[PDB]
Image 1 (cartoon, helix red, strand yellow):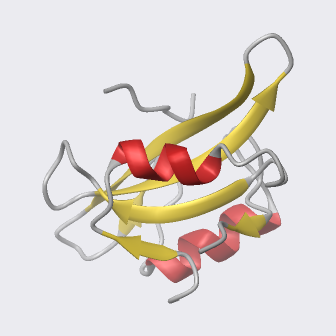
Image 2 (tube, each protein chain N blue to C red):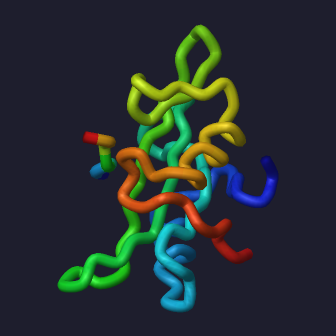
Length: 7
Length: 103
């Protein structure tokens, strides 16, 4: 599943 | 802590719970990660126009020095500290945290 990363 | 820690709940349920249309943007909860055992997750609801209500999930990894982080530049000794910080300023998050999800 995809997870957001802080850029 | 307490209010916002939902325990061992699934990605599916957190989305089910965060996609409530009366929740303001930035409603959140902290759960365990289903995919990465030992790591937690921060599920924030967002509202992009065009995609509508949605949920961003961020993995909170822990270091053996005993600190949590989503990004590494910012580390916290405490998940309640992390929540407090991301409530005061988004600093990379899709939206600052504004609300402990209802239930």
